[PDB]
Length: 49
RNA sequence: GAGACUUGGGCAAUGUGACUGCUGAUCAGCAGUCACAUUGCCCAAGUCUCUU
Figure 1 (tube, rainbow, N blue to C red):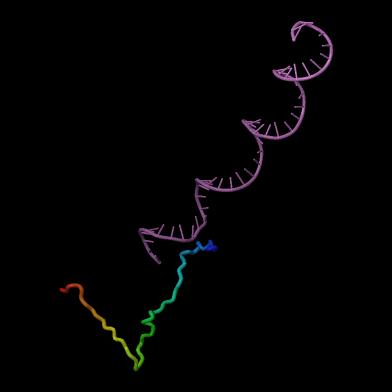
Figure 2 (figure 1 turned 180 degrees about the vertical axis):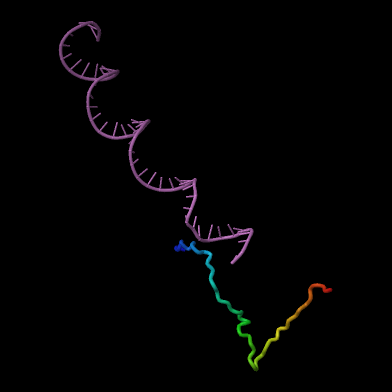
């Protein structure tokens, strides 16, 4: 904060890293190990023509 | 005690000369701070338009 001259280029933007969630962090099955198949459902809400 | 004189004492009134501080009013000269105003350098920041 003592660097009060920080108003010169306050429009500067920086980069950041990204990371997948813990569950998605290497959930790949191993041969011989238990696997969880999570079913996907697509229920229609709109009434069709 | 009074009248007057002599000296002295007491009180009072008023004036005169000098001193030490205290303020009052006016005037000049000087410094500093704060604020406003003029435009510009000016980046931040949002909106908007063009467009990047």
